[PDB]
Length: 49
Length: 48
Image (cartoon, rainbow over all chains, first blue to last red; front, side, top):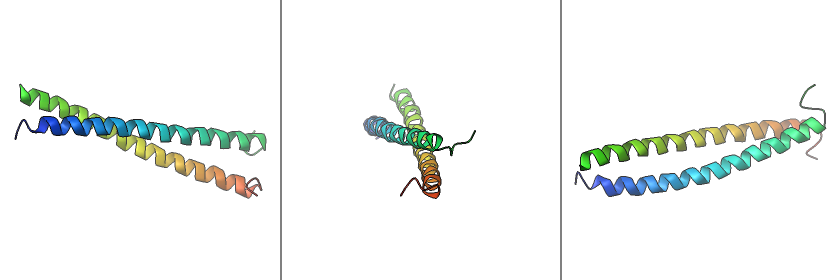
């Protein structure tokens, strides 16, 4: 149907909105690991000066 | 009518799909940054 696109898009967009939140969490976990590693390298003299 | 509603839903859909592609790309960049930081820790004897 032409109008039949309505439900399909609605439902895809809900799934994509959810997937964005999962990907934001996983991206944040990786940022926190990067910060942890940068601190370890800095405390050990390996991040410059 | 329905044609305008559909166009708006398609606009939202591409904005969401673009954001997902960005987060997948940035997350893979971050995994590479983690691998490089881990290699430098291993090389300096901080990973056993």
